Image (cartoon, rainbow over all chains, first blue to last red; front, side, top):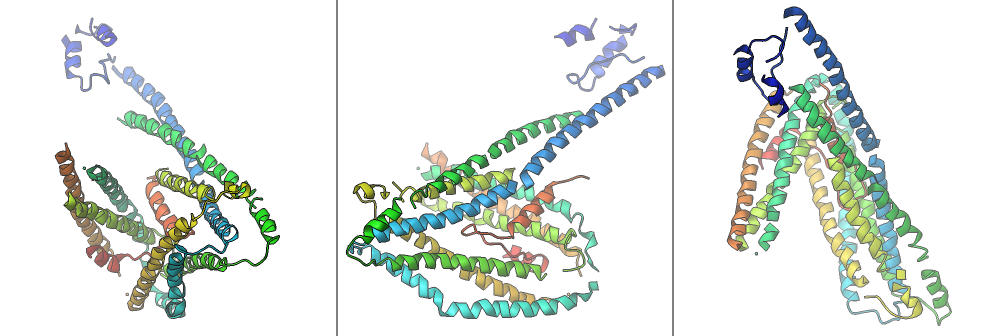
Length: 203
Length: 136
Length: 118
Length: 42
């Protein structure tokens, strides 16, 4: 109400019909009320405030900037813990599996063990010499490594030159990819929700 | 006009810090699950060297164990291989434009491929869902 | 940060299965100790990792076979371009557009079912 | 201007293609331009 409180009833010696009209004319009434301004020093006035104002804007913007730096600094070198954790996980998985496995040889023979076991064992046999043998290994892995290197040798030279290039003009195409990235992230999260609004179609 | 942006900057900044905090203390704790679950896989090194000592004061022999020892190596082996395959892929990627790796060019080709890959999913996870609808 | 959220959800999910295959393991053999039995787990989970791996092998040969199609290419591989970047992006702005089709495509499809249910 | 997004992106995508032990997710090879456009088309 208090707005209502001061804006009417007029100010400084400002005419009541003009003061009215600044009220109607007001482009943006909550953010704003009509305030009487008085010739040049008053504009001087305003400017002094503007500057006053300017410095504080700049600063608060700096505060946001510092907090963001702190978050990024924590985040960027914190990837370390995530990666470390993950590897630790895999090693613990290997030990888990190894302990799990030895609890099935020592208590378990017993020499009982078979049944289900062979099926495990059929699966395992298959996968294992699949792999082996033959085929794969050899041929493939190192026609690829034999190969890779020869392409390396050759690519270097052809290079030589060409002749700079065009790097340069790389800045943006920065920029336009940013905007494709957000569009894709919205589509992915919408598909994910789609099938939600879907298991529920589990109906 | 700028001040307003400033506002939803402040906003969304301290909700980023609500973020990180959180994820921060999270990582401690996922981390602690890793110190506990470890001390005590052993002290599971009792319970398993006891069985051993006990089992030794038995008739003898151990058996049908090897298969597992094979299974773990077999399971383990490919893990070996994934690394090698990774060790290749990186080399292949490395073979690619000189005088400046630090340019924007490769930046745009990386990012862009990231987009293409993500788009792919979106495709048939979508097609999935689109697929899936038929039963209904 | 955002990105950092999925990473923990993965580490979450995982320490949880490993806490545990670690728990199907202690205290199971803890019993033993007194005298009980926990075990045809494994057979469960062992054959479960097999099934797990079974596919991972296929992934390996899928990637391997891509590499050489890729190298293969690299061999063809060897010659200038600003226009193409543009040509790419005008295509991406089409590709995203049909994909959106499909997603609304699906989304509305789901929505239909959801409507039918009630 | 001072931007840090696509530096995240590139970041991500950088951080993407290199490794690791993660039981599944192996680094991917990056195409671009000629092969990619066609790849997009498929």
